[PDB]
Each structure stands twice: as C-alpha cells, then as structure tokens.
Image (tube, rainbow, N blue to C red):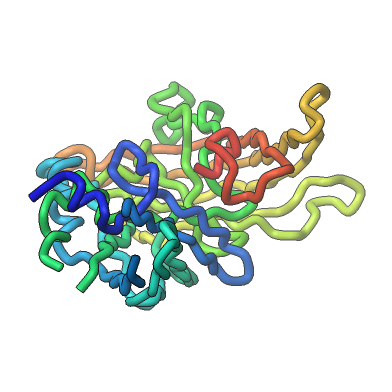
Length: 309
C-alpha cells in the first residue's frame, strides 16, 4: 500500500464542524425542499463508475466518539422518506470533480431530534476500506431547518420564576426556536435545550399569525400552547410580535432584520428535574432576534450572524 495509490481514489470535499458533520440549511416554506450538492473529488485515463451509499456503521462510531455515554445527544439516522440521491455516477476521464445531488424533503421532520445522513463514496475495489477517515470517503450531513421566525433568539428577557412570585429563578441568554412549519416553531420551557434528555416534555409552541392586533398598528397576533398535559401549561396572555428591517448605514448590502416577541406569560411545572418532586414555575417576558443578512448571498449561505444557525 502507498499514499499515492489512495490519493488517486475518490473522496468527498466538505468542511465539517466540531461535531464531525456538515450542516445543510433547509428552508421550511410551503414545503421543506432543498437539493444539496455534495462535492466529490478525484485526487488522480478511464471513466470512473462511482457508487454512493448510506453508511450503516458511521453514526454509532461518531456518536460515541463525540458524546460518550450520552444517547440523548446522539445523531439519529435520517429516515429514507426524507431524502433521495443517485446510487451511481460516472466521472468522465479528464474530469477530477463531480457532484452528488441530495434532494431533501423534510415536511413533518421532528426538529426536536438531531438527524444525520452518513454517506460513503466507493468504486466497486477493497482499497476504499483502508484508512476511510484519513481519505474522506464518508460525509455526514445534518439538515438544519429554518423559517422566517426560527433560530437563536435572545432569551434574557424571558424570566423564569416560581408561580405566584417574581423572584428570578432562571433565564437563558439564548433560546432556540425550532421549526414545525413555515409559521409554527417551538422552544423548550425550564432551561431545556437540544442537550436535555427530557426536552420533549417541555416543548412550548408559538405560531406567528398574519393578523394585526390593531389595524392601525403593526403588532401581530400569536398563538402559544403546549401538547404535554403533564406540563400543566397555563398561559395568561396571547403573545404579540413585530417584524422590522433596515439596511446598515455603512455596509449598504447588509440587512438588519428584527423580530421582537412580547406578552409571554405562562405557568408550567417541572416534574422531572427533582427526584419525586414537582416545581411550579412561570416564564414571563419576551424574546428577540436581530439578524445580519448579507443580501448579496442566498439565505442558505448566510453565516451564524443570520441567527438561523
């Protein structure tokens, strides 16, 4: 075996993040459809018949190596109904690049879970089973849903207290709004995040309606609710929101988009943090997002200052 013999074979060309995955940004509009083009490289006379397959052992290894014995943090294999990709491609002689188009169709995807699609490239040649990690034979794609109202919101003004009192008990600097549809999101009550094992129990849904509070003003109505009856969710006001944008004064291609949610006020119970006990809490206040968007780039190519990711 030689380094050059393995550097004449085919690989994927991605820049994966800290958790070993490549994020694929997918807008949830009327549908949640996006074709992601995964780059293929030939590091070195004949046409190549390349095969692509779901790699059945990748996630179990990546999950343990990144998260240890914490199954609540693990990536789950994205079910087959959510994607399609060709199993084969011909790379002509003289061409050192190719693209694997993956069509994602994520309507109804549960955004409380971390999904991943592990893919390996091969030539049907046992040399693809040697040092597969070193030679980037496998890519792991993580779909990130987004809509106009989703992502990393400021949470410091959404104050957690005991029910009946105003003494501050908890708050979070960031509260992520996860996607359900183009207008419905959810966040987690009681400081829960994507990293909490019991997070589904604390889901609080928000719906951004297109209805004005007052025809003369630009406040818009919302719905707020919970599905978990054990939360004993009880809201005292329907939230409202305002959406505004302005172009930056000096970077004239840069758009600032603001969403401010107000009038959140609900009681809920934390029945899982404390052994054999229940805490009656309340969250009151609001949420906000301030996005920086480079209007010269597609939405999916925005950086994290977009706050969608």
